[PDB]
Image (cartoon, rainbow over all chains, first blue to last red; front, side, top):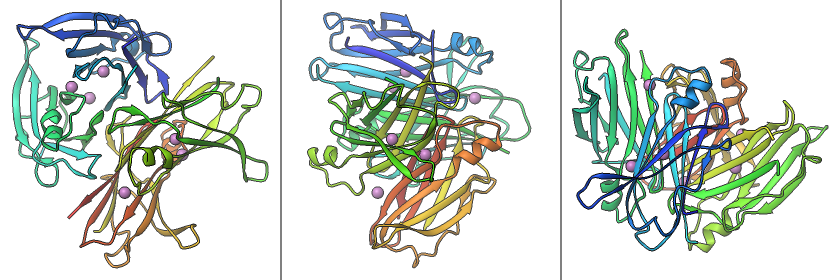
Length: 116
Length: 115
Length: 116
Length: 115
Ligand SMILES: [Re]
Ligand SMILES: [Re]
Ligand SMILES: [Re]
Ligand SMILES: [Re]
Ligand SMILES: [Re]
Ligand SMILES: [Re]
């Protein structure tokens, strides 16, 4: 699995479940094309977005929509969208883990890149 | 100032200097319209983005051009930008400070509101 | 596995391998007793520190020593020690993941707590 | 000031006020000896910890009493403290700023050095 997304709640110390994840890939005409999507599991993780065959070199956008997570906590969120943009596999295939840490007034995102 | 941005470099233990910062405000059509931009100072800070009365209630996005910052230091980073979205509500005069902590593969952004 | 430690390098975007991890448990006489130890794997993770049977309620210290990781990168570290102190299983058994993110001038640590 | 500490609360979007901060310096016997302590102000900052000439080269530890801070807000946090260790080298006059970003289950600490 070359692309994994994890979402965690820094206030609760908990995985963020049912967060919608969208992955886009920049096309030849400089438009964002859809690439993959899913929802985070009970562990706050989403695997199986792509395979090494499909996950070619390129510029990718990963966007999360946390509305359902906040709703289920009885929270009315001020805003519920985060996105990072990165270049993938530019030095050959890698496995990527993108982790987001959520809080009402702060956001952190970390990438871990390994050679498989 | 009602709005300030502060940017730190975790690799060098220093303010992030001359980093470009763009502020957008969500318009009625749900598009991000330009609001203000600037570059961080020698102390990593950016002031003078808006007056009190132009800084109206709404949804703002701060977009920090971290890719160009790291490449100027000879580092190939992960992210294209560091970003934060925050809501400005209608209140008495409040100060908004956006603080960003940058590394090549990780960042954190925080919105601090003071009276 | 109720206690996991992960260590990552925010400059390289890499797991931190061969980081020594020491876990202590506060004793009746208010001294730190040894509890478990290990070294992080190639994935920057250490599992198998303890079992649910041994990992009782208590006050625990987790300390890492990164000297070997910095050495292997050809880095002469200014300092190479980090520690957190936490109370475990106070509301019944939990699984704990303690993650550290390393950089020359910054340190971050995050705890993820799940009910198994 | 040569040494300042700044502490932010990520849950409330505010400076962390009245937080106790202890600074230690490693002694010859490799023990942490007390160096200075204080509480953060209404802006989350702590100055006046040391004079320039008392802030000698060495290895310093800053220990922020986050457990009591969160419990005063009715929150049971994970960590006992937020900590950072930094080395002060012998240089020309330098400013050291320790910045801490606090949440109940996560924190980050950064040492920023300026001339
Ligand atoms: Re990005
Ligand atoms: Re993300
Ligand atoms: Re906000
Ligand atoms: Re701690
Ligand atoms: Re740790
Ligand atoms: Re340092």
